[PDB]
Length: 111
Length: 49
Image 1: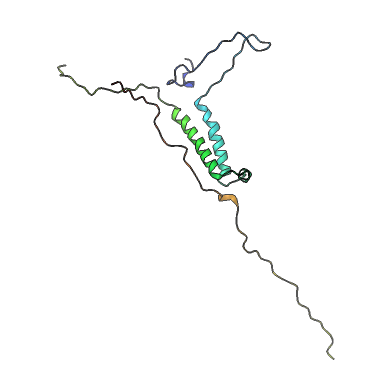
Image 2: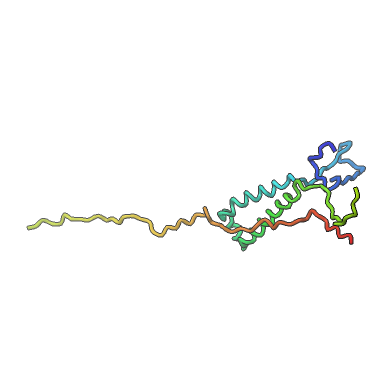
């Protein structure tokens, strides 16, 4: 509620809580944080610009096709990755706004 | 009498290069596939009869 630009709103309330009796060694209390945020897509983009800089020239690739691999396999691969960056772009700034479907239906007006 | 010899010629073949192909990987690939197609996934049908 104090950092709402850090959470998605079309997915209500974002967290599952669990409360265990048993902290780790030597310690009063703790917790793990795990999460997925729209930030993460930089990993996939990073890998992809760095892969493309090899593959556009087939550099290092001979070690790969040396074990019987086909260049199209990495084409199907990279396109699966750029579809993933496209998916976090579908969900990046996606609108929590309302939507509806409406009757095209009128009245005898007198007001 | 003509006195003997006094004539050699040089052991010489000039050097050149032929059929040395410029086979560098600098433009070694051209192939592409798009990062998936455009789709809508955010909306309900609202099909209440």
